[PDB]
Image (cartoon, coloured by chain):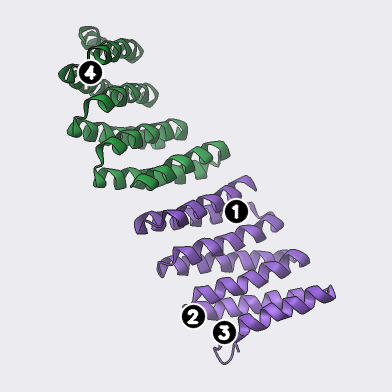
Chain colours: A purple, B green
């Protein structure tokens, strides 16, 4: 699906992949799934569709929270930030805040305070866009995510 | 007002605010629109001098009186002057790194802006409220950031 660009099929497959890994209690499949999600996100940014990228990152944290691979968590958070930057350029603040919702979930496991800081900075950019759109429910969500980002520091 | 004018000569801004508190007390008991207008304009010049002194704290205390009066009076251009000055004060509070005073300055500014309904003011206020919240996040004080959130988000919720 990645080579085809048929990225919905990559999202579908990832969901079943974590289903299998979790129903088995697999010791390492989590790592492969997360590394694949990083590739999926990188291509989804080139394809512009961040909403696929967040759905893939949804699987990525679901796995990574079992695994505790610190470099993978750091890469995943970096990708979630990049996804937020693109979602802001696309004006999709709703996808941007959900990208941050994943980012903080992962960063809370990793303990990367500079990532939590960068997440809060990005959340302020999201809030600025949400104000500019009048998407004040999304500003509320961005504020909740920032409260997580601050409180876990 | 005479005592306040004397304080404007003398430069004791705490004495000036002590007088101004009684001034609004009398003016609010009277309900005279022009007396309120005068008190507000006096408070504005007190704040202008407090900014030259760099005393942002007492400037915000003066602004708290200014909104107390202005909220009774409905002088729209005075509310605008107050809001503009409240942002000028907040910008100095940011430059000083006193985000607590800056957040209080925003809390005043939004109170006034909600009476005024001036959309450009409201958006300029919310803009600076995010700037204040950004600098409060750079300081990283969580309880101050909960306030910075609460104020900026409520401001956006009116704007």
User: In percent of the image, x 79 and y 73: which residue is there?
Assistant: A22
Going from N to C along the chain, the mark reached first, 1 or 2, is 2
Percent position of residue A47, x then y: 48, 82
| Residue B26, visible in the rendered structure | yes
Q: CA distance from mark 1 to mark 2?
A: 26 Å
Quadrant where the N terminus of chain B sits is top left
The residue identified by callout 3 is A7
The residue wearing badge 4 is: B39
Q: Earlier in the sequence, mark 2 or mark 3?
A: 3
Q: Which residue is mark 1?
A: A116
Alpha carbons under labels 2 and 3: distance apart: 12 Å
Q: Residue at x 56, y 92 (%)?
A: A4
Q: Chain of mark 4?
A: B
Which element type, helix, strand or loop, lies under badge 1?
helix
Q: Nearer the viewer, residue A60 or B35?
A: B35
Residue A103 % position (x, y): 60, 61
Dot 1: few (<14), some (14–19), or many (≥20) neighbours within 10 Å? Answer: many
Q: Disc 1 is attached to a residue of which chain?
A: A
Find residue A17 and report its horizontal and vertical position in percent: 73, 80
Please tell me whether mark 2 or mark 3 is closer to you in this view.
3
- Indicate which disc residue B61 carries: none
Mark number for residue A46?
Answer: 2
CB within 8 Å, label 4 to label 3: no
């Amino acid at each position: 699906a990645i080579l085809e660009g048929d990225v919905e099929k990559a999202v579908r497959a990832a969901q079943e992949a974590v289903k299998a890994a979790k129903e088995a209690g697999d010791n390492d499949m989590l790592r492969a799934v997360a590394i694949a999600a990083l590739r999926i996100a990188k291509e989804a940014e080139k394809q512009g569709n961040v909403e696929v990228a967040v759905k893939a990152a949804r699987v990525a944290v679901e796995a990574a929270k079992q695994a505790g691979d610190n470099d993978v968590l750091r890469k995943v958070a970096e990708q979630a930030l990049r996804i937020a930057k693109e979602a802001e350029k696309q004006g999709n603040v709703e996808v941007a805040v959900k990208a941050a919702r994943v980012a903080v979930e992962a960063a809370k496991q990793a303990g990367d305070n500079d990532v939590l800081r960068k997440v809060a900075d990005q959340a302020l950019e999201i809030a600025k866009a949400a104000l500019e759109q009048g998407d004040i429910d999304v500003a509320q969500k961005a504020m909740d995510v920032a409260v997580e980002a601050l409180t876990q520091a | 007002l005479a005592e306040a004018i004397a304080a404007i000569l003398e430069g004791d801004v705490e004495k000036a605010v002590r007088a101004a508190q009684e001034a609004v007390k009398a003016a609010k008991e009277a309900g005279d629109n022009d007396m309120l207008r005068a008190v507000a304009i006096a408070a504005l010049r007190i704040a202008k001098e407090a900014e030259k002194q760099g005393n942002v704290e007492v400037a915000v205390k003066a602004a708290r009186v200014a909104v107390e009066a202005a909220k009774q009076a409905g002088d729209n251009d005075v509310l605008r002057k107050v809001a503009e000055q409240a942002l000028r004060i907040a910008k100095e509070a940011e430059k000083q790194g006193n985000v607590e005073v800056a957040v209080k300055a925003a809390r005043v500014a939004v109170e006034a802006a909600k009476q005024a309904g001036d959309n450009d003011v409201l958006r300029k206020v919310a803009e600076q409220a995010l700037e204040i919240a950004k600098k409060a996040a750079e300081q990283g004080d969580v309880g101050v950031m909960q306030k910075a959130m609460d104020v900026a988000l409520r401001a956006a919720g009116q704007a």
